[PDB]
Amino acid sequence: NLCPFGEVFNATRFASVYAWNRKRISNCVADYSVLYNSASFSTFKCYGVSPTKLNDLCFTNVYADSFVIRGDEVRQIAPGQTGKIADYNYKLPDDFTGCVIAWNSNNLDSKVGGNYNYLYRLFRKSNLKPFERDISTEIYQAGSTPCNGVEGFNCYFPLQSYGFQPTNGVGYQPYRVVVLSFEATVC
Amino acid sequence: QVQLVESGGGLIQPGGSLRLSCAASGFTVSSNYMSWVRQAPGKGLEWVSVIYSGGSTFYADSVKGRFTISRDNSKSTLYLQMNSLRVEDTAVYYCARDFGDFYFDYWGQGTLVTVSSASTKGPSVFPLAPSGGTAALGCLVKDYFPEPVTVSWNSGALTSGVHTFPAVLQSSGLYSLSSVVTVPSSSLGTQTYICNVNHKPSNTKVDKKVEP
Amino acid sequence: QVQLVETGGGLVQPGGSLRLSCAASGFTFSSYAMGWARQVPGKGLEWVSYIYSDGSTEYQDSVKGRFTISRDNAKSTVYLQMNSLKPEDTAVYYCATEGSLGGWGRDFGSWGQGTQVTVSS
Amino acid sequence: EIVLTQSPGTLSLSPGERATLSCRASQSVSSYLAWYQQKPGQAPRLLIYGASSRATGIPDRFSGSGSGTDFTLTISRLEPEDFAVYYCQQYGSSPRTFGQGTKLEIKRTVAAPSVFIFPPSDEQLKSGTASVVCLLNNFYPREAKVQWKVDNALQSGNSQESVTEQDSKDSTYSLSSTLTLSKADYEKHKVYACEVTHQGLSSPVTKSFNRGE
Ligand SMILES: *[C@@H]1O[C@H](CO)[C@@H](O)[C@H](O)[C@H]1NC(C)=O
């Protein structure tokens, strides 16, 4: 049985980083060399294994996490990194074994007035643990007085929205990301 | 309200260290982004360092490897540890509350950090003696360190038409300054003109009479 | 911090060649890999060539044989020799570097401003 | 490295008029642009964020416009406290960088400088050094050219200027140019002269003295 990668990569809607998506991959066979040759995949870098030897291996269980960041934040989706995305949205462990894949999606995910559907968490009192998903919408208490569900002075919405216009630089453009985590399910 | 009070600035030698701190009131230091932004004398603004709410720290490349930003929530304090300092680093350093590593909505008052190889020296005062309808006279306050000095005319009596120029930093590493005042010509033999120079860091006090 | 400047773009008539160069700054260029990509207006950004620190290269199949990626560590520079150009190849070409050092494979971490190449008629 | 180029460098206006300051970016920063006011001797104050959004407690007459690489700050009816230095700052790309500033300056009629020249004092000559001082008093606009001539040799690379801030009452400037040189070099030459070029002067004005008179 061939593996449902088309369901992941070619999906119609993509999640925002703070609420990233996570699909299981099990009991399947997959050809990774076809993927590795895609012109779309600006980033296709593995940790532990090498993309070349992916077809000759197999893994106990595989996860495909997927989300949308902006081009110059793709470098945070890697072990040992820091930044808003790596700290507060999606965190890889230092011992990560898997692959990070990213392609530019300027035509699907940008919009001339701005595409405000994609969000990321700006504020959090402490960093995310590896593979943690925080989806809290609670007003962020930046001062000693509580916020009582109303944003204001020292009381911020924890989620900000990307602008995503197609005319900005490549670092500002939306990139779709898929993270394959490898632990016999998928060979 | 929000208040931010810096301290720790002063004078310091190239190669030396210096710790700035910023007392913060009105918000949770540990819950916010906070930055240090410096301004050199007569120049624009430069971002130096940031610390995130989660504790990640980032540095401008000119200071990275030498500056370290940190904080202490119990004390409501931000700190900037400055090692291996250079003349370049001479600036007013502002502590600033940072809205999400984007812009600075609340600034402190600044603490001045001057990096010099010079040492304390009191100024020498020399007369700038008058020589159209009005005559100009003054005093030249030369070769002093550190800043500042204060100049009066007739112990505060004469203030009208007085210009005390900002100090200039010369190759020496010492500062120089002028105070001038314009008077009617007819008043030159009539009236006495004494300038009063005060340089507290050397306890220098000088009352110089200026005559044609 | 990291700064990458592309030049060399311009007008070519079909069949002609074009040498693109990208100057690097702000990192030990010796240790990082390098890449060249291109964006067609309205189409997704696509990678064309990659070069590792080991000199190992990758060429994407749509530019196979015709392009040649190379590097001079002495001058922190990467080059892209475009022979046998077609109107399919007109785009804004970008130069890129790894984001971080670990790992195996292509990594377009930091981007240049880009230079335009246009195949004429 | 996004570079912000603010123009003009100096902006000269009267109370009541409207002011248009521009900031241009070396690459598009979308709408990630902010504006600051800095009054003399004070800290910067956030005026506007997100190109157009007014900060809390900022009055009505400050407005932000533009996007991408072109931005404008507009001040509709200047009160006298609005005469300060203004900065733009981008946060679309790292590292964050500021503009170099636009100074908002009270405008007045052109006024020509009064020129005075001061020889070194005998007291200072015994010190082993000599300072010649040239004073340009109460003039406007600020731009002034002082040029030292020692025995008609146009002298260069050993003078320091310093200028006052604009006068609160008559909005003029004053400026001092100091020519410093050894007692020996001072004694080498005879005629010491100061030539001033200013917009209020039909022709450059020269004030001179002969060493030892
Ligand atoms: C995704 O869609 C494109 C275009 O329809 C197709 O050529 C490609 O093979 C698909 N890839 C996967 C992994 O489904």
Image (cartoon, coloured by chain):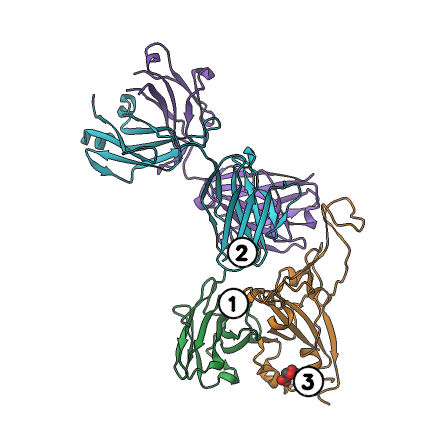
Q: Secondary structure at mark 3?
A: loop
Q: Chain of mark 1?
A: C
Task: Give the percent coordinates (x, y) of residue C74.
Answer: 38, 69
Question: Residue most toward the bottom?
Answer: A1
Q: Is residue D113 above or below residue B191?
A: below
Q: CA distance from mark 1 to mark 2?
A: 14 Å
Task: Give the percent coordinates (x, y) of residue C89.
Answer: 48, 80
Going by the numbered disc 3, the residue's amino acid type is Cys
The label shown at residue C111 is 1
Q: Are marks 1 and 2 on the same chain?
A: no
Which one is in front in this view, the residue at disc 3 or the one at disc 2?
2
The label shown at residue D95 is 2
Going by the numbered disc 2, the residue's amino acid type is Pro
* Ligand 1, image quadrant it occupies: bottom right
| Tag 3–tag 1 contact (CB < 8 Å) | no
User: Which residue is rendered at x = 69% and y = 55% of the image?
Assistant: A123
In the rendered picture, chain A carries what hue? orange
